[PDB]
Length: 247
Length: 14
Length: 134
Length: 103
Image (cartoon, rainbow over the protein chains, first blue to last red):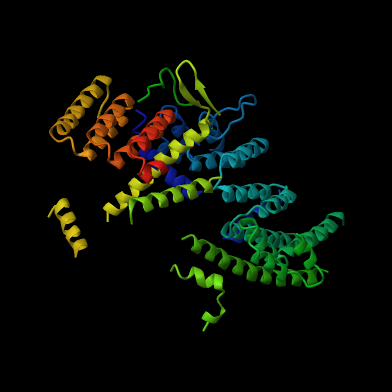
C-alpha cells in the first residue's frame, strides 16, 4: 500500500522545491546577518522503507521532520545522547542533516555535530571549513569567521585548497568592508568607521601574498633549501633577512 | 515489506 | 573620510581581482600536476672508469650481496644427558631470517614470472631457444 | 575447492599417488622430487617433507640445488637447529663445494 505513492511523491517533490556566484553567496549571507504534507508522506514510508535512495528524496524538502527522522539513523553519544554522524550513512546525507540543524538555528547542536563531522572526515576538510565559515557569516559571529579562516589558512598542505580558502577570505573582507561602508549612508557610526578600518586593514592579505604562497611550500617540503631562499628574496631588504636565515 | 506499520497510521499545518 | 575610504576600497578591490586571478592560475597548475674535459678528471675518477661465470665465483658474489642486504637493515651449552649442543639465539633474528628467505623467494619467483609473461607454448620456447642458439 | 578435512585427505591421497608413481617410474628427475617435497610443505606436514628430501638425497647426494632447497625449507619454517644439523652434514659430505659453506 505504500509503494503506490512514491511516483506522485517524487513528482510533487519536483514541483514544490523547484518553485521554492562566489561573491554574491557571501554578499547575501552577510545581508542576512543584519537581523508539509509531502514530508509526512515520506516520513510514513521511511518507517519501513528499504534503502537510502528513498531517503535522498526526503532531503529535497520540512526541517523539523527531516531532523526528527534522521535522529533514528544517527548513533547516540555514550553519556550526552547527542546525535553523532555514522559511516553507515553516506556523506551527502550527513551534510543534509547538518544543514537541517543549521536551518533550524539549533546552534549548540549544530556546532557539536560539526566537531564530530570534521573529526570523522579527512579529504572533506575544505568543504566543511567553508560551510562552517558560512555558519559564522550568516549569524552575528563575524569575529570567529576571521579567526576560523586565519587558523585554517595556516594549515594548508596543497596549493589548490589554499587557493580556495585564500580567495574566499579575500572576497569576504572586500564585501564586508563594502557592506559596512554603505551602512553609514554617533556611537554605532563610530563603530562602523572602526570596523571599516579593521576589515580594510585585514586587507593586508594583498600585501602578504607571496609570504603565504611560499609558506604553503614550507609546509609541504620544509627542508628544501631553494624555497627558503625564495622566502629570503621576498623580504623588504631592511636587515629583515637575518630573521628568515635564523629561522 | 517489513510490515512494522501494524496498528498505526500516518499523522494540521499539512 | 568616506570619499577617500571608498576610493581606497575600489583600488584594493582591483588589486584583489588581480591577486585572485594569479592565485587561480597557481591552483590550476597545482591541479594539472596531479592530473678536452678529459684533462680535469682526477686519478680517482680515472681508475674507476676502467671498469665501465663459475659456480664458485657466483657463490662468492651471492654471499657478498647477502652481506650487503644484511648490512643495510642495521651462548652455547652441551646437554650432558643427551650429548647435544644447545644454541641461545634470539627469536627476532630467527624470525627475520625466515621472513627474508620467504620474501626473497617471492621476489625471485615473481621476477621470473614477469620474464615469462613477456603453435604451442613449448614450440615457441623451442623456437626462442633456437634464436638464442644463433 | 576443499571444504572439509576428509576432502583434504582425498586430495592429498590423489596428489601423493601421482608424485610417488612418477618417482617410482623415474627416480632421477630431481625437480620432480623437489616439487613433491614442496607439495608436502604446502600441507604443513614437515615429517613427510623431510622424508622426501632425505629420499631424494639418497637418490643423488651430489646435487647442490636439492641441498639448498632442503636447508632453505628448514629455515623458512624457523627450524634453525634442524637446519644446523643439515648444513653441518652438507659440508661434511661435500666439503669442496663453496656454496654450502657460504650458506
